[PDB]
Amino acid sequence: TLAPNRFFFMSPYRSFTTSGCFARFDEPAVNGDSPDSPFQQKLAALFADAKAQGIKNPVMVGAIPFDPRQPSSLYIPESWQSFSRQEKQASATRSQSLNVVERQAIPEQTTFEQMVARAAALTATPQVDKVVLSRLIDITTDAAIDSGVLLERLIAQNPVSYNFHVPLADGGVLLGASPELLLRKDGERFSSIPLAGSARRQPDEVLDREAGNRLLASEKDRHEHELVTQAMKEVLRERSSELHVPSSPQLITTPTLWHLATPFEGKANSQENALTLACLLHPTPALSGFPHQAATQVIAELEPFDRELFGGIVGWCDSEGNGEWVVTIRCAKLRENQVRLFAGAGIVPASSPLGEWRETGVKLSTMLNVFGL
Ligand SMILES: C=C(O[C@H]1C=CC=C(C(=O)O)[C@@H]1O)C(=O)O
Ligand SMILES: [Mg+2]
View 1 (spheres, rainbow, N blue to C red):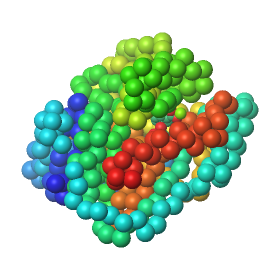
View 2 (view 1 turned 45 degrees about the vertical axis):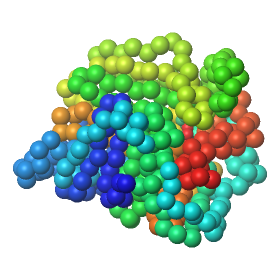
View 3 (view 1 turned 90 degrees about the vertical axis):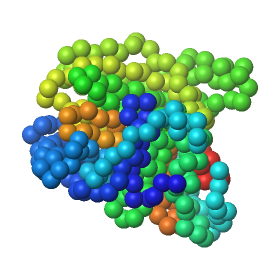
View 4 (view 1 turned 180 degrees about the horizontal axis):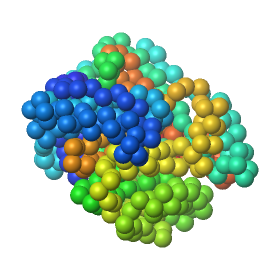
């Protein structure tokens, strides 16, 4: 299985692992949409240094937190190794039986439901339209957790998603099956596929198609979604030479959920790379809200924890400007015998406190399934 000190990224674009560590890069990504930012300037310096020291085709990999004024968890590895996503899907079980010493919802149901009610109340006012609220599950086991076994189970349960495994500076691992592309850049073209709006999958094909059709006709979820795509369209319109965005979202699936999705396909100029555009977008109203600053204030006032890397982005950038960044969701941080799971939900005036408790619950089940819980 995969050692915990290696980066792993599985995607229809590039799928690869890494080995070694040439240089860690913890510069905050704030203002990274600007080529003149210290983030971009130091990124460029570090790539030039890697090549000067004989690293061919250097890549920058890792995770950027929800709040990009915080330090990043990025690094250049010594080497990288492509693999076939299709072959991995075909190949991908247990090694240990784990006991649960403690399991704690943070916050608990009544508290989260009151948070949702407060956020919904705020979204009824002119000052904010949408706020994404989140919660955690902390689990302590009695034995160190085999992150490599977990990764293989994660892939087998989520063969199609953007599956990642990120070594962290504190010895932990960030692992997840993200369904949400934030920014892919491949030559001059770029894409983004925001997700917002959720309905539970059903085991029967008839009920399942009905859930999807219900989601597409749901005013609440379509509103929750259009607040994301309108904000993104406005920003991207001024930094793209062409941009195609469909008028309506389409249905996509994970193993647990239907989501509404809108693809963005654009062309960018020579000033841009995968991280300038990813930092321009991140976080969208899928993960913070709209307007962004007002939403993050409400998040800070209501969540009894710091998100850190949760709700950030994870992926990679090379020295030519190509890269891929996905939203850090359906994910967990683990270290030794401790695990933290994360899930959020976009709150609007039509949100129900119980409904959003349940929505975040279904989201948490992706990683609960990986652990066998
Ligand atoms: C913050 C999360 O979901 C975001 C992205 C997909 C669906 C969402 C929703 O439908 O509410 C959220 O905007 C999460 O999965 O933890
Ligand atoms: Mg939602």
